[PDB]
Image: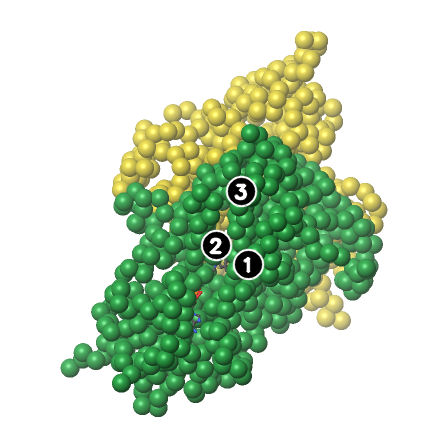
Chain colours: A yellow, B green
């Protein structure tokens, strides 16, 4: 009955569909489990109707990013604003010392650069370790050329990379930690606008929401059969599975009952199954802090508070005689606070004019914070200390809790918090995390190869976890969507 | 009659000194280091100036400290005796435009950020690409601007190309003369400023038999006697016969060998003549002219915020309008033309504020060709030099919370006490700074011809004969270790049963 059935209406699924229509292919479907399209691209609304991408927010690698370039064209043609280049000089804040960025004496950014260079040389990749292990090796080998404060603060500064992978430094693969940024980043002014434009480019009656596909079977007759949970069954010539990696991973697990899990028959070939042993998922999370208005310096749109550090750490590094001795010596034995991990804050006031902070968090904090997302009081109590330090470093004062408003003129030039928004990607069965990430010992290529090769001729895969360029990214998934559709598109046309 | 030696090293620069050090280390005896100049070190030279202040007028930094073998040795020494042999002086760059003033770490210009994109653009332009035409650095930057105009502000288009040019001071070549392919090269970590490169030269110089060193003997000719021997002639009339010779003279000096006219200082007459692969390699690699000017002041009465200061050459809003209106690369190249004297604002200049890194009240400035050749051609005219640089010096002082400079060469104001200039483009034993690439050059050719040698007995060492550390002091150092090791290996067969 159907030419192509696309499972998942995230950017990958949406582009594929868009591509099929664009190539004259008819009778296609887009089966999405959620009651909306967009997938991990979701723009939510908060205080005074302000909007925020709770999922993806930036166009990365703007030099080669095809999706971005496409958006660039549109903006060049209609003069409308679709994005803003918000890269900025990073402001680094330590609870005790305050700002430590661009410091004439700490020069942290410079040794951070040597650090990355150090990592590159290390894997040019005899045995992988965690990012934490690599930073410790660097400090030990280079301590002769590092001051005390550099040894203390640099390791905390370099962990901003945790916010790129969504994983604590002790959980992150050192080999995959440092990747090349192909140019500046462009903050999307509505990834929902990207979703809508693509979504509207194909037959609206093609979309089926709330269709949780439960099983996919390759009928030995040149036809694929798809069954959504409710009971509706379909048959198509080609199927493009774009469900996230974490969801697809349920398939290779026993006890088919998990929300989202699809039953493949025959099962996914071994090359696919094994791929999951060297892939894994990350948990980038988001907390939005909405204030009445801006009353703090807009020197930069990029701010990072560093986890607390100690002088005893420096002493231990200075005295350690070798890697092992350093390791155990570091073993020094609770309760997580906003200062237990680095936190990345986007000061939307400078880049968008909106008096709000978009904060990024990583596992294990993410899971914990998203778990208490309904408890605004606790949320404020948890982040209040880093929020106050930031305001102090930005020439302002302590934040006023106005989540339960009480108009008070006393709040002259005081920052007044009106709302807090939290992501929920780790508890959403259809996402179960943020995007593919590497634990030490992983090999991302495996999954790319297997996914791109597909289960077979009719069973294809798309998604941010199915491509090399832009892997884990919106544009990566977008392109993976075009890939599968164009391939199927050429195949149907050749049937002449 | 002509004395017999196992190995004769021509040149007591770092390659040659290391060669000798290695030979002795491996037990080779009866060797010789013949140096034309009356001192050792070559392009490693530390001079004295006002009040006995010391400055390296040639090489100054240990580059690529994460892997630099020469730096690691020095570091092992300091780690043991606690003596200070170097200082990590990397810092946040201060950028100064004549009209605008400081444009570094600017919340709106964000030049540093787009500069990073620029180098990435360059990387994507050549990185692992076969069949790509070269073009000049200047042209690469123009292309970037054109293709990214939509994502750059006017001020970024105006100032960015001028900041990018600090790379001219890494190559000693003006951006229009420089090969874009070879412009960007990775740095293996931070740089360490040597506090007496001459102390590095002396240690290596003292690590071998002191009677080996013959200064003031310029070598005139090298002859391969088809009897497995090499005859070497010093101009002082002495003749030597050696089983092996390691030639470490500068690439610019060796180039003289492929031309007629023997009475040129430094030129070596080769018989038989240098193989065609060597002669022809001189067409695929050239020589840059990094130069120096040391400005010594009475005392420090300026901000020590940073030790790294770069003055940007003048730029115009007209350029921006031209990038904006250009229809394509071909049009841009065209429009860019008009109808002129060279001043201190005609090219970027790099100033090391030694007051913060060493505590010495002096600026060490780097300059590039063609400016270097002109400035050295007037090194003797101190009043003229001061007038030429006075404006960039004044602007720097202004930006560092101080006042115009007072000529004190003959309480709150900076007083210039002395000006020192390099002489590399004029010294016939250097004839330039170091090997560099012109658009279309292929450095690999020379390295291959050099490391392979003229033949089994006639070898080459020097910054121009090796890949890792090419053009650098440690590259020259390693090249010397290379040839000496090879020779030790071969001479070792002598003791076999
Ligand atoms: C907090 C956060 C921030 C991010 N920031 C950025 C950024 O700045 N830049 C960037 O490039 N990327 C970013 N990303 C990653 C980016 O969002 C993803 O790469 C991209 O959206 C993945 O697209 P997709 O089409 O593969 O899947 P979409 O989620 O991403 O999901 C595929 C679809 O499958 C559906 N589905 C699942 N199971 C079933 C089923 N059984 N039946 C039917 N449908 C099903 C889902 O509901 C979903 O709509 C971020 C991610 C997170 C979590
Ligand atoms: C201004 C300037 C700044 C620099 N800064 C740095 C820096 O910061 N870091 C870095 O790593 N490098 C730097 N360099 C480069 C570095 O100095 C050289 O790579 C290195 O010193 C070259 O060593 P060499 O042994 O090959 O030659 P040395 O010049 O470099 O020359 C070999 C020797 O041959 C002798 N000779 C020549 N002809 C004859 C002859 N006919 N008979 C006998 N002897 C002869 C010469 O007098 C000389 O002593 C700089 C160079 C210049 C010019
Ligand atoms: C600026 C900080 C985070 C921006 N978003 C990052 C999105 C994911 C980029 N690719 C990550 C891949 C991880 C394996
Ligand atoms: C340190 C600032 C400028 C120049 N330093 C000297 C660099 C010498 C090596 N340059 C790189 C490659 C040369 C062939």
Indicate yes or no: mark 1 CB to ligand 2 under 8 Å.
Answer: yes
Q: Quadrant of the N terminus of chain A?
A: bottom right
Where is residue A323, by image quadrant?
top left
Query: Which numbered circle lies on residue B57?
Result: 2
The residue carrying mark 3 is B417
Instruction: Report the Cα–Cα distance between label 1 and label 3.
Output: 24 Å
Q: Chain of mark 3?
A: B
Instruction: Report the Cα–Cα distance between label 2 and label 3.
Output: 18 Å
Q: Earlier in the sequence, mark 2 or mark 3?
A: 2
At horizontal 32% and vertical 85% (from top left) the residue drawn is: B229
Callout 2: few (<14), some (14-19), or many (20+) C-alpha neighbours within 10 Å? many
Query: Does B166 sit left or right of A489 as displayed?
Result: left
Where is residue A4, by image quadrant?
bottom right
- Res. B360 in view: yes
Comparing labels 2 and 1, the label whose residue is closer to the camera: 2
At horizontal 48% and vertical 54% (from top left) the residue drawn is: B57
Q: Earlier in the sequence, mark 2 or mark 1?
A: 2
Name above or below for residue B128 compared with residue B157.
Answer: below
Name above or below for residue A186 compared with residue A309.
Answer: below
The answer to whether marks 1 and 3 mark residues whose Cβ atoms lie closer than 8 Å is no
Name above or below for residue A103 compared with residue A270.
Answer: above
Instruction: Report the Cα–Cα distance between label 2 and label 1.
Output: 11 Å
């Amino acid at each position: 009955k159907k030419k192509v059935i696309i499972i998942g209406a995230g950017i990958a699924g949406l582009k594929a569909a868009s591509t099929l229509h664009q190539n004259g292919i008819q009778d296609c479907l887009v089966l999405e489990a959620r009651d909306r399209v967009g997938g991990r691209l979701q723009t939510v609304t908060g205080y005074q109707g302000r909007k925020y991408d709770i999922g993806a927010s930036w166009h990365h690698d703007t030099l080669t990013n095809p999706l971005f370039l496409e958006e660039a064209q549109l903006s060049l043609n209609d003069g409308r604003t679709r994005f803003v280049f918000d890269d900025d000089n990073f402001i680094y804040i330590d609870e005790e010392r305050g700002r430590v960025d661009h410091d004439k004496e700490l020069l942290l950014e410079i040794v951070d650069n040597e650090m990355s260079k150090f990592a590159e040389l290390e894997f040019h990749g005899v045995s992988d370790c965690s990012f934490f292990q690599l930073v410790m090796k660097y400090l030990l080998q280079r301590r002769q050329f590092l001051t005390n404060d550099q040894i203390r603060y640099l390791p905390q500064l370099c962990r901003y990379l945790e916010l790129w992978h969504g994983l604590d430094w002790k959980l992150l693969s050192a080999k995959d930690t440092y990747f090349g940024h192909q140019g500046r980043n462009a903050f999307a002014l509505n990834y929902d606008s990207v979703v809508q434009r693509i979504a509207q480019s194909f037959p609206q009656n093609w979309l089926k929401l709330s269709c949780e596909v439960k099983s996919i079977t390759r009928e030995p007759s040149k036809n694929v059969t798809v069954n959504c949970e409710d009971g509706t069954v379909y048959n198509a010539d080609y199927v493009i599975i774009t469900v996230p990696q974490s969801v697809l991973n349920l398939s290779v697990q026993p006890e088919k009952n998990l929300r989202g899990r699809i039953e493949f028959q025959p099962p996914l070939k071994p090359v696919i199954q094994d791929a999951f042993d060297k892939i894994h998922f990350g948990a980038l999370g988001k907390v939005i802090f909405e204030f009445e208005e801006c009353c703090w310096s807009n020197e930069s749109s990029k701010i990072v508070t560093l986890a607390n550090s100690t002088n005893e750490f420096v002493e231990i590094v200075r005295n350690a005689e070798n890697l092992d001795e350093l390791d155990s010596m570091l073993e020094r034995e609770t309760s997580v606070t906003c200062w237990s991990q680095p936190l990345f804050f986007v000061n939307l006031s400078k880049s968008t004019g909106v008096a709000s902070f978009m904060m990024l968090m990583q596992a294990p904090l993410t899971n914990h914070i998203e778990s208490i997302r309904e408890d605004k009081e606790r949320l404020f109590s948890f982040f209040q200390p880093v929020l106050n330090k930031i305001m102090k470093c930005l020439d302002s004062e302590d934040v006023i809790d106005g989540m339960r408003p009480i108009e008070n003129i006393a709040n002259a030039n005081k920052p007044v918090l009106r709302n807090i928004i939290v992501s929920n990607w780790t508890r959403d069965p259809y996402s179960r995390g943020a995007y593919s990430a590497c634990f030490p010992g992983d090999d991302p290529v495996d999954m790319v190869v297997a996914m791109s090769n597909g289960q077979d001729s009719r069973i294809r895969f798309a998604g941010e976890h199915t491509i090399m360029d832009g892997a884990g990214c919106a544009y990566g998934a977008w392109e993976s969507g075009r890939r599968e559709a164009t391939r199927i598109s050429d195949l149907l046309k050749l049937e002449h």
